[PDB]
Image (cartoon, coloured by chain):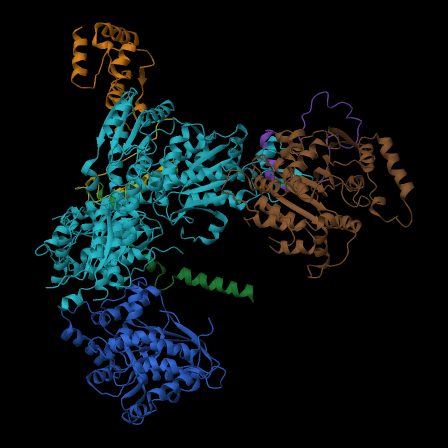
Chain colours: A cyan, B purple, C green, D yellow, E orange, F brown, G blue
Amino acid sequence: GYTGLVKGGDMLKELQWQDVRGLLSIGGTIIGTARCKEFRERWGRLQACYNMVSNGIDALVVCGGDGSLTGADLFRKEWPELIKEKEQYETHRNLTIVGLVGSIDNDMCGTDSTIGAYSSLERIIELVDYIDATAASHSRAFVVEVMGRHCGWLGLMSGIATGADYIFIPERPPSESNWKDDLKKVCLRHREKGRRKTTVIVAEGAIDDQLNPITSEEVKDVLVEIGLDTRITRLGHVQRGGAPCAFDRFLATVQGVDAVRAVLESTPAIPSPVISILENKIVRQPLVESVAQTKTVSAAIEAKDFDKALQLRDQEFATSYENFLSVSKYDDGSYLVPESSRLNIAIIHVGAPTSALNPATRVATLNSLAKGHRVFAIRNGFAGLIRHGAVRELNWIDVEDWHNTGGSEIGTNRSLPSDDMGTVAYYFQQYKFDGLIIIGGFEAFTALYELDAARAQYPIFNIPMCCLPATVSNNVPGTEYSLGSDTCLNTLSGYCDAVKQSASSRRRTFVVEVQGGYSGYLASYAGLITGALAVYTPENPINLQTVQEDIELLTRTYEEDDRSGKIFIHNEKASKVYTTDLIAAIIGEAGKGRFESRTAVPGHVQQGKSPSSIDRVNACRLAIKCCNFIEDANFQVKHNANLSADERHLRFFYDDGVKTSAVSGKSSVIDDNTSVVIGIQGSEVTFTPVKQLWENETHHKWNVHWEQLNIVSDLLSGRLSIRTT
Amino acid sequence: HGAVRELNWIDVEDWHNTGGSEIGTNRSLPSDDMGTVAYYFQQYKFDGLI
Amino acid sequence: LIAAIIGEAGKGRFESRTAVPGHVQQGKSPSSIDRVNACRLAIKCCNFIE
Amino acid sequence: GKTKSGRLILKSENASKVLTTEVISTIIDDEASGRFDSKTAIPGHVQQG
Amino acid sequence: VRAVVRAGIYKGCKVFCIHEGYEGLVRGGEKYIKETQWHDVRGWLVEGGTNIGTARCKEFRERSGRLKACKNMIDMGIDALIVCGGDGSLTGADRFRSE
Amino acid sequence: DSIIRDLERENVGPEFGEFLNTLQTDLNSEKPPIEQVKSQLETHFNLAHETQEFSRKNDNAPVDKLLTNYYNNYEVNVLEFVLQMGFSRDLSIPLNVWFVLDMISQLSTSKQDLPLDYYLVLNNSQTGKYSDFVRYLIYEAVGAEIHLANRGPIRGNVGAGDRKITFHLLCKKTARMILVGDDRETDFEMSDRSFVTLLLDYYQRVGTTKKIDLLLLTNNFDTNMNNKLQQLKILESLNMLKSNCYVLDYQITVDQVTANFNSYVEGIPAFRRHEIANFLKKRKTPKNADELIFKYVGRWNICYQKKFHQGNISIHQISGYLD
Amino acid sequence: DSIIRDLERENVGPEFGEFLNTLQTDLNSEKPPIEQVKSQLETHFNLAHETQEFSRKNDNAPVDKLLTNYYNNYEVNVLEFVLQMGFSRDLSIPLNVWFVLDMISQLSTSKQDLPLDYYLVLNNSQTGKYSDFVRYLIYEAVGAEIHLANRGPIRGNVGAGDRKITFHLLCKKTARMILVGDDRETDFEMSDRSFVTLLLDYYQRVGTTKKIDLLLLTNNFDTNMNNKLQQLKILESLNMLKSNCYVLDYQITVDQVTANFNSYVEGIPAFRRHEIANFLKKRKTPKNADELIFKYVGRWNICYQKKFHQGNISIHQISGYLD
């Protein structure tokens, strides 16, 4: 850290292109870290300055947390102060300083997420997943002491990701007077409703509204006096170690490239930035403002004004807290709606499996049941419905352990209502469904469209319907994110880490085949995060010249190496000629049998055992938004009308000859806005009607660009350098 | 209108003599809305039609 | 696959081989049956259209 | 009626040079007559760990 | 448990799963002593903890419960007991054997 | 804003302008913008004494809740096609505007309703000049910042029920605009008789087959033309009222049309038959002959049921039709 | 204007930035824009002596009408795909540019033409910097007030016949922009060798399956890579030229490259086959091996036929493919 900048001599050493080999699967730091201590004093910062000028250092890149950036900000403020005892002065007169947020906390302002935050969250989830993975006992409780000194983000996200009963966060602390009694209430309420795996999450900075800390031991004692055998689990240093997760690998690599750009793109007129992330877009925020904003949250908490602090957190934090609070309070009965307003909700899993299916179905069932609606799960897709009438009613107890479980508990398949509309329409009428959630991929998108189009032929289908996109491919129109894709990237990065290790008299080069459909997104993302040499995709042409170029890069790369083992990412649908098998075969014969080429096919393992935290958090956000849409009273039959039972089921009535909608009161019975695709655009959730999306989509299973994934990966592998000499 | 009426031994009374229709007759076709005809056939669970 | 199964048969008893005449099936010169019929039918084609 | 736990067939690469993972699976589909399908899982020489 | 249920079934004998360990054995009945089928222990390899369940039985620590448990086995027609547990868990089974 | 200039031109008092300037609603509060306008209205115009006297002089009737009084929650919330047939002379312009707003709020107490269409006729010079001011208020009351115009319906969401509405103000200015084809120049005289018949000409041309279920009658200016009973007879004639329509008739002052209205409505079929014929024998002259009162004479063959009465505030309902 | 700063930044004399101020087309005028800008270029830069000399030192060849004379109106106006493989090292940047416009004007004399595609490649660092100057020049020449861009083809009409043209300028600035997905920071080395192979990478990834029917060849700077014979050789291998493609080779200086070139183009098949073989034997090293020249080696079986030769300027056409 700063110690090497203060005692800067042998502590300042150059880094070569080969020195940073395989660092994308390592963590923490090879440069090593240190606490801000001598850099807290002016004479220390003066010496740090001398060393930079003396060693001809013109730019500094600080990758650290709140404290490290507060220091970087103070060093830039105090830099115009250069004491003299030389051309060195005019040369190094203007400090070029850029900041990267390396923090598990996720405390820093201006950025939606900091480097290490999701990985640390993964470590928490890793542990709570073991706790959850035991068959339930009659009177058991578990306390998880999570790290993160300055921000309740980890505590919150762990709460959502694990389905915790109660959480302790510095932003919204409980009363000193009755937190124990409120803890008891919440827990016993859930226990009453069927919960046997009572879980509480205590943050590192957990406090009560009078600033008194809340230890996990304090919390244990509360639950023990409720007759529960409580067990503390302290994560400790586990939360800071290990390989970064899929998102962090992307986040650090991308922000890291921009940090270098920000240095070059600098002038004294353009202020010193903090490389931040906002609506999945990398942004350059000013260091001055970001450190200042972050200090005001710390101040708010210290000043016992926790309202200012929670208000001072981004929408990401706000929406997440609101969601955790909602789900927790579903047991209240406060969500309950009048008898007349209660509906029959259908959930179906259309497409190949993703680990994200059960968590999403869980949140959707609880949300619906909380209102008094009846939840019916169409088992084994449309085929299960058509062939066997496979409908199963869900209750509070049925949902149990689903937030952790992968695949489908009801069954998922790519069969379409097309197979027999008449039969689908018969069953929808029998079970009297008033709303439908199609969780799945391109076939869930297809089914939504087909059923929407069938509204004409079958009145029963004129209900609100939605597609919750869940797929590994990220090939569904109407969203930037499909549930299960982050789990897949995590599964792939880990898989490749084991590939490169087995590539160290066995094997040298590996052609890892990525199954991401007809879209190069999966392959491109995977390539960036695994440090793949070449990435084969349907979007980019494969031929004798391209192949020769790929071989040349591999050849030129290997004739420099002295940790090794190289990978190529081949998308299953890239070429009907140059397949994973042919590419591997050409690499082998290359250099008159120079290296040993091997194929690797993770394949159906890409769905993963447990959904990632990004998948768990989003499955919950979107399931909530699905229910809010289909169960919206605006799209539902009006109860103060002279309507017959059949008129209310048909959702239309004939008034004075005119066919009127029992919902809108309008002459046009069919509303196209009721069949919608619920997805993410930036940070915001979007509702997009199928009819419009269906003309836009391609027969190549769907305009969309992830080009910069490929640009950055090629810059960081030898590609861009070999391509330009 | 979903205009279905159940008939019993007593309802049939004096019909062998009477002209026109007691239930109503018109040239409208199921074409007008198959879906609605099909919904009603399913509700009333008709096993035969004259 | 058939050739591959024959080969592994009898714990490697006989040597199985594939043969693919393929596009050679058209032949260098038409057979006499082909020459005779080509003439009969060509005559009948012309007689019809003309 | 029973639990749907899923089905696996494990085939050591050396068990058959002719009846390979991919060949075996295509035979299963042929013989299954649409009642179920078969898919392969070929992880590769990554199993070292 | 999956192994015991299947092995016993294969060897041609009825397998009963005593839910809540000694508590279930002392309380007895269909409530705790359920007949288990081959397909009932499906995919239990992956499952963590105990699907049958464990419970600390205060009564079985005394001759009061040890006798009640003995009756329940003869009533259920259970000719043999298989305990899967810890030190005291097996010492208590050993004491039950001599008693 | 143009409205303030317009009111100064029509000779109207500044009060109305000053009301619009300070008139503001905020759909960031639990109170609906309708109850919010109602509050601002009862404040600026000091309508408390006038409302108090309006009731106390109609045998203490709950004027603040007449629909909520007779009908139940369902009964009232089903009503979806209202016709307020002029303003009352006995009420000050703001008092009438509050009554239009008080009525709208009652018909929108539930979130389970089918949309409402409210028609308001401004049948004379004493009320027609206020139309744009009314249309602006309704606009704020309903909050049509969803997606104003010099003509057309004001769409929006009204009441605690937050019900979808579509308010229509059918006045002379609007009728002129229609006639000229939206030409700038609309200064020409329009008879109150001519107006009613053009309202009929708009309806018959639009082809509206939606029936009036609440009919609001009162003591309008031009008693000669806007006769409460004559208006009833014309709607009875044209099949414009629903089979089970509701006729709510209010006023403070009592007149002979009030005697004749109640004698017609409450009358036996033989009486109504005679009533019509004797108006036609008495009043039909070859010079008068073409007037709508001699075309759309009303229907004796109809039946009513007196549902509510509290000193000159009555609610009858079409009980039957005899064919 | 932005170009004027770029130019000062790239050590280029202000003359260029000064020309882009005095540079403006009259449009309405009888004289076609290309010819206007062309005559404006001659004036500002005094390209009268150098043009005359370029003729003089080439046995008084018509360096103003090289195409026009040789070909008939049909022949010149049938040419649709043109590749200009650099700028001569023997002529100034304004003479080189002028010549581009002059060659362009020559193919657009007719109003009975299908569209023209013109590709200018500015391969070395010497000319590369003037891409934007040339782009603002071709923009004014065609008058792209039809519907400039940082990248991309300039489309408009051109010459005496208003023939729709699409001028493409391939340089390293555009190549860097491409590689970095249009990022602000395009400051990185790129060897002329890399540049040639990336041009191809683009032809194969863009998809282009159209054949060049007039190939303009000269003596560019950086001959180690931008070698005339080596460029021809490459185009022959990649099947990029029309079966009757015309190959124009202009310049003033005679060197060994020109001898090697002429002996290859005009050589008997046995000479060409050996020319290729012995180059590979003599020049291929295991370190050299990867270079494009070792892959896209030329074809001895392509025959040419001399069409024109006025000392140092020649036209040969492909006359057959022996197979």
Question: Looking at the image, which residue is at 43% across and 86% down?
Answer: G73
Q: Quadrant of the N terminus of chain F?
A: bottom right
Residue A243 falls in image quadrant: top left
Q: Is residue A628 left or right of residue F84?
A: left
- Kindly tell me whether residue G314 is visible in this rendering: yes
Q: Is residue C31 left or right of residue E11?
A: right
Residue A104 drawn above or below residue A211: below
Q: Quadrant of residue F276?
A: top right
- In the image, A697 versus G148, the foreground residue is G148
Q: Would residue F48 appear left or right of A278 to someone viewing this image?
A: right
Foreground residue among A141 and A382 = A141
> Is F235 displayed left or right of G95 in the figure?
right
Determine the residue located farthest toward the left in the rendered image.
A10
Q: Percent position (x, y) of residue A444?
A: 43, 43
* Above or below, comparing residue F247 to residue C20 in the picture: above
Q: Is residue A563 visible?
A: no
Q: Residue A181: x percent and y percent?
A: 33, 24
Give the position of the C terminus of chain F as an image quadrant. top right
- Which residue appears at 49% of the width and 51% of the height? A692
In the rendered view, tell whether residue A212 sits above or below residue G44: above
User: Residue F300's spot in the image, x, y percent?
Assistant: 83, 35
Corner quadrant of residue A685: top left
Location of residue G160 in the rendering, given as x and y in whole percent from the top left corner = 46, 84
